[PDB]
Image (cartoon, rainbow, N blue to C red):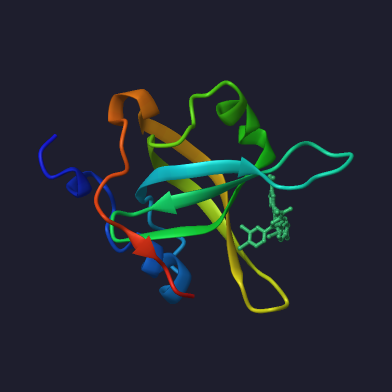
Length: 123
Ligand SMILES: O=C(O)c1cc(-c2ccc(CNC(=S)c3ccc(-c4ccc(C(=O)O)o4)cc3Cl)cc2)n(-c2ccc(Cl)c(Cl)c2)n1
C-alpha cells in the first residue's frame, strides 16, 4: 500500500555488493528477466533487481528455480524475498549474485509497476 518503496529492502543492494552481507533476507523487486546465452545445458536467467534505491543486473537464478520463470510466477514487477543467495566474483573483479531460494510475496500482476525511482548501482 501507500509509500510503495517502503515494501522493499532499501539499501540491500549496497549491503550485498559492498559489505559482503549474505545473511540478510532482503525484499527486492524484479525489474526484468532474460535468458543468458546457453548451449547444451539448462537455460540460465539473469535478473535486473531493485531494492527501491538502486537497480542491479548482476543476478542469476539457480537452475532449480527455472520453473518459477518458465511458469511465470517470477516475472517483471513481482516483489520477492531472497531467502538464500551466494556470491561469485569473476576474474575481472565483477560480483555476481546467484539466487538460490526465493519467495514471491506479490505477483507481477498485483504490483504492476516499477516501485520508486531506483538508479543503477555503480560497482
Ligand atoms: O550470455 C550472456 O549474456 C551472459 C553470460 C554471463 C555469465 C557470466 C559469468 C558466469 C560465471 N558463472 C558464475 S557467475 C556462476 C557461479 C555459480 C553458479 C551456481 C551455483 C549454484 C548454481 C545453481 O544451483 O544453479 O549455480 C552459477 C553461475 Cl552462472 C556465467 C555466465 N553473463 C553475465 C555477465 C556479467 C554478469 Cl554481472 C552477469 Cl549476472 C551475467 N552474461
